[PDB]
Image (cartoon, rainbow over all chains, first blue to last red):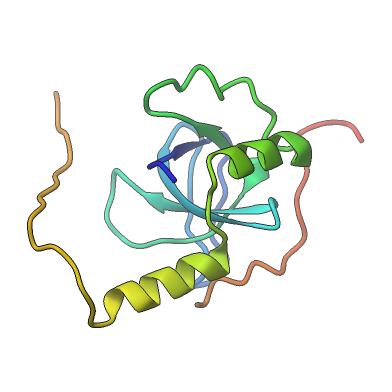
Length: 120
Length: 16
């Protein structure tokens, strides 16, 4: 799938080590979903680690067209479903296995460099 | 994985 991004619309404070506090108006990076109820969003601004945030506390959008999926109803299991299905977003389990196997020793490419923007 | 959200799915701010 493509590097989709989600934006928090409500302040969701973490509860356990498997949860990450978020605020309304923040930028999070989606990694996977869970039964179309929970979404795996990570911090983009600050630096800490991946957590867990419900779809009812986030808004699926696109860095290319954030105004396209800005009207969508994440709450509606139907809408969120078509989105996750269309974009072909991986699930939590799939994400865990992917990262686990990806971290292991295998073929890869050293070439490649990425960085974060910075203005004002 | 440590990412098993077995918790319930919360609803949006509305009068159900």
